[PDB]
Image (cartoon, rainbow, N blue to C red; front, side):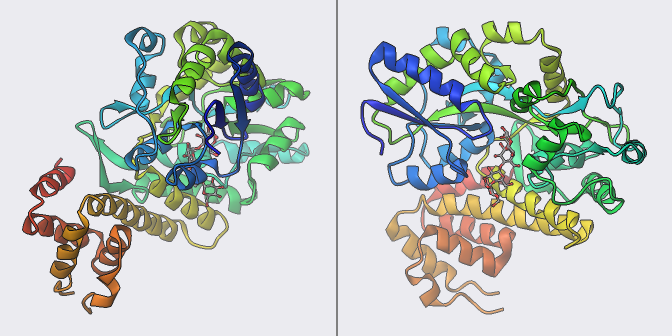
Length: 457
Ligand SMILES: OC[C@H]1O[C@H](O[C@H]2[C@H](O)[C@@H](O)[C@@H](O[C@H]3[C@H](O)[C@@H](O)[C@@H](O[C@H]4[C@H](O)[C@@H](O)[C@@H](O)O[C@@H]4CO)O[C@@H]3CO)O[C@@H]2CO)[C@H](O)[C@@H](O)[C@@H]1O
């Protein structure tokens, strides 16, 4: 589509898209510009595919962790808020949408997972993960269960995996080390082992997912769930009297959720960038605009200071921010999707008994490190001129060890297939050393010097 004089917006289907459509109708009334809100499945995987063809929505909403990869691939317009508009939003929310020094999206709202609990079944929720088996043994006798939440998406199990030490990529000196992946350390093993023990002891079912847990909680069948602010609307409509509180500790350490900033990026290919700017700054990021969305599904702690001051008086929002401060803002680097895919497979395989915890997590660390390295090496090879990539292949065609890389394999391979061949054949660490040295040899000392700086700590 991408037609001029219309805005198309994509937002995930668990968000308040009917409220956002109401903000779109006000824009249309005031300006004559139609706004279409859609919620495609897997919108966050479809956006990079269609935007790289010059198509897609004008505006895309997702948590900020996806946006670095979109920006690195050139799919997002840099946004240009004036100083006066920037002062309307909290400074840490602007940081979450900064990539390579540029603002690449409008931050909307700060999301963190909380422990949600049914006050009639459980007037005093647990402070610890460790007491949840004893607490479930009690509720079973009453015909209930202690805790159901989505085990299919690692976003929901990460708080526990990280509590005693798990991490995605090691952070220091303001930069993330994509070679130092923390999904296989002692603390991650301990958290996932606890989760799987909960399943093997029949306190949880490995196949619980979002809709199952949400239904069970909102029907009064389970005393607790783990969810974000978007889920409160549906509990409000049910008969459940709930509270929202800090996640349980594990081995005495806070559960550490990955905090998302819901963010609106502008497609690089859109011919409507100025209208999208006007819609986001003057209609959405206002008291009325955010109230319209929030009434549909709550946003969490919004980035807009004037509205957030009213929301911050809600103890549910107090709890959301308490959990946020116990966790960490997600990285936005392009390698975050590699981390998430690897962890997702590990948690599903351990929970279903397909693999042990130790083997699931050992494979997740290898998979994440390999995919992260592929991402970086691809990006660098894409910076070679086509004539320099040809010289590169001749250099690597002579690289020894069991067998070499045959000429026909490289002959018509582009930068991504070349990155894959090198990594498949040499492993991530050697693939990168060979490519770095080859950049020096074919006289791209700019790539050589910048690549050297990647691994310095
Ligand atoms: O094939 C496996 C699955 O692939 C797809 O899911 C991927 C995503 O494409 C990745 O982006 C990532 O997802 C992260 C996500 O980026 C991160 O923001 C967080 O998502 C929260 C969201 O912030 C929050 O607002 C609310 O919507 O809940 C989301 C979690 O459900 O965490 C996600 C990780 O859990 O990783 C997954 C792979 O796990 C695809 O969409 C799936 O349909 C597919 O099965």
